[PDB]
Amino acid sequence: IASYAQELKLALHQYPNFPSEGILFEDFLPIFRNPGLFQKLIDAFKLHLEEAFPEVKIDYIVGLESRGFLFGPTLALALGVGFVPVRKAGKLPGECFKATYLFEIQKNAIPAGSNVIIVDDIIATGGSAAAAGELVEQLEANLLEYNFVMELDFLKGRSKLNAPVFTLL
Amino acid sequence: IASYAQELKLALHQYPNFPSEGILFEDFLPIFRNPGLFQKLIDAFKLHLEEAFPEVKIDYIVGLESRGFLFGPTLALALGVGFVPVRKAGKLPGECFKATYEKEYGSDLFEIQKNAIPAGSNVIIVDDIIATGGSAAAAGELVEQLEANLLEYNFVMELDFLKGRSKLNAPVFTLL
Ligand SMILES: O=P(O)(O)OC[C@H]1N[C@H](COP(=O)(O)O)[C@@H](O)[C@H]1O
Ligand SMILES: O=P(O)(O)OC[C@H]1N[C@H](COP(=O)(O)O)[C@@H](O)[C@H]1O
Ligand SMILES: Nc1ncnc2[nH]cnc12
Image 1: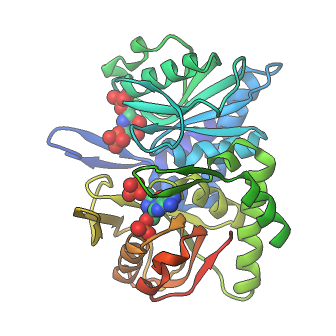
Image 2 (image 1 turned 90 degrees about the horizontal axis):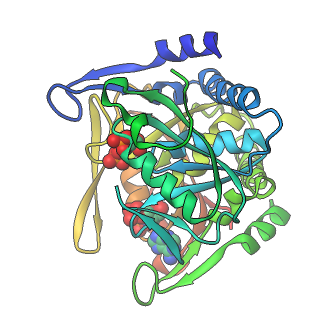
C-alpha cells in the first residue's frame, strides 16, 4: 500500500489555476494511461479492503459520477462484486432515490441489508460523498467505508460524513 | 461472442419515455451489478478485438464521458493498454484539443488532453450507445487532432434507425 502510493503520487500531474485562479488541481488521469500504474491503484484499494474488512463480504462498490467511474467498476470486478453508479439528477432511468448537496441512485439496484463501499477520486467539501451516503441509507444498505484516491485536508470534507474514510494518497 | 451477447441482451432493462416522450431508453447498468455479466461484457470486447486486430498493437482505449467510463478503463486494463478519457468542455486540466457536436437545442463540446496520446498511436474509441453519432464523431475529430490512428469504434448498443454510423469515418463494431 505504501510503496504503491509513492509511485502513484509521482504519476499525479499538478495544474495551477484550474478550474479557476488560485486552485491547485491534482490530475490522476496519467495513472490510467499506464496499465502498470492502473493495476497498482486497483491492487492498493483491494489490499486496503482485505485489511480493513477481512471477514465482511462487500456486496457492491458505489461510484460517484464522473471520475469515480474511472476506477470503481474496475475495483468491483477485481473484488468479484457488483458496481452501482450514483449519478447527477435526471441521468438515471426508472424509479430513483434523490439526495441534495442533486444526486440519484436506482431503487432496484441494491437490496436492503447490502454492505457497500462508496468510491470517488477526491473529497473536497464532502458534499457529494455525503449525498451518496444519504442515497445508500434510503436503500436501507450498510455503508462500510468511503474510499478516495486523494483528500484536501484543509477543506475538512470528512466532517460532513458519518461513516469511516480511507484516502490512498 | 454470440452466446455472451444473448445473456447480456437479456440483462438490459427497457424504460419507455425516458428522458422524454417517445424515446425508448436501453439501460445497460444491470450488467455492472453482476460481476459474472460484467466479465462477459469485457471478455466479449476483448475477443472481438483479438479477432479484428490479431497483429496490430492497440496503444489506447479512448472512452467517452460518462457511460464509456463504466467499461472502457476495465477493457483497457484487461488488454494491457492505456486508457484516456474524452470529456465534456472545461473538465480536463492543461492544454486540450476541442471538437464541437450538435444536440437537440444546442451545440456542446468535447475535449482531450494534448499530452495523453502520442502521434502515431493506434486507438479504439468506446462508448455505451451510438444514437445520432454526434458524440462519437466529435471523439474521432479529437483523435485526428492528436495525429493518432482510429482503428475502430466499439459500442455496446446501436440505434439502427438513427443511422449514427453514417457520421463516422472509421469502422464500427456493436456488441449487441
Ligand atoms: O466535475 P464535477 O462538477 O462533477 O465535480 C467532480 C468533483 N466533485 C467531487 C468532490 O467535491 P466535493 O463534493 O466538494 O467533495 C468529486 O465527485 C469530484 O470528482
Ligand atoms: O450524457 P449525455 O446527455 O450527453 O448523453 C449520453 C448518451 N448519448 C450518447 C449517444 O448519443 P449520440 O451522440 O446522439 O450518438 C452516448 O454517449 C450516451 O451515453
Ligand atoms: N435510446 C437511448 N437509450 C440510451 N441512451 C441513449 N442515447 C441516445 N439515445 C439513447
